[PDB]
Amino acid sequence: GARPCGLRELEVRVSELGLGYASDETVLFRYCAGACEAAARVYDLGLRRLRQRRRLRRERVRAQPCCRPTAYEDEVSFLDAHSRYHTVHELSARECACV
Amino acid sequence: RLGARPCGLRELEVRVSELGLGYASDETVLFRYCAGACEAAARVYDLGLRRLRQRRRLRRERVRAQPCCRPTAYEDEVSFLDAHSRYHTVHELSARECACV
């Protein structure tokens, strides 16, 4: 439990993705999930202190690392409704990191 | 909120003391950071990820299904003189570049 930020796999039906595809054919879906406890960055620390001090302009400021894809899979093909092989691009994460 | 302002680089003059990094310096530095809205919106990966989270198919993990305004690059270093005339170097203090991750 509570594992670090990394690549995750899950077999899904294309219809389950909520992309508007009728097909029930399965595709392997890859995604970034996990924890970002790689010690607070000097940038993040400085930002949090300035944030509580009302020094920062009233705006949405993220002073915490995010587990997100740094690269995406080029393409995934599945048989669609019109029975043609349809390609969806950048569906799955290829690489993950804490940004 | 429509028209909140896109994710981008922001600059503000600060004393090194204000950062709370433990340095005994009153030197003014230009602090560069990433702030703003990230309404990408609806990247196929994000749309699929949000939908799978609704079905509770993601193993209970944290999962970040939305883009974040974060630095993609950091300024190499900041150098200053503390009160006791001691030279200090702070690495990766400022954002060099921003993006919706």
Image (spheres, coloured by chain):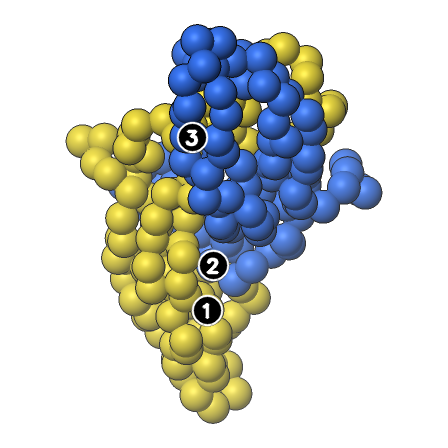
Chain colours: A yellow, B blue
Dot 1: what SS?
Answer: loop
Which of these two is toward me, A46 or B43? Answer: A46
Instruction: Determine which of the numbered discs, if any, sits on residue B90 in the image.
Output: 3
Residue A21 shown left or right of residue B11 in the figure: left
Foreground disc of the pair 3, 1: 3
Q: Residue furthest left?
A: A1
Residue A54 shown left or right of residue B87 in the figure: right
User: Residue B21, relative to residue A1: is it above or below?
Assistant: above
User: In which quadrant will I find the C terminus of chain A?
Assistant: top left
Q: Are marks 3 and 2 on the same chain?
A: yes
Q: Residue furthest bottom?
A: A84
Amino acid type at image mark 3: Val
Relative image position of residue A79 (x, y in whole percent): 41, 83
Determine the residue positioned at 73% across, 23% down: A58
Relative image position of residue B6 (x, y in whole percent): 72, 46
Instruction: Determine which of the numbered discs, if any, sits on residue A26 in the image.
Output: none
Amino acid type at image mark 1: Glu
Q: Which residue is mark 1?
A: A90
- Determine which quarter of the picture holds residue B4: top right
User: Residue A7, relative to residue B80: is it above or below?
Assistant: below
- Determine which quarter of the picture holds residue A76: bottom left
Dot 2: what SS?
Answer: helix
Distance, label 2 to label 1, CA atoms, is 7 Å
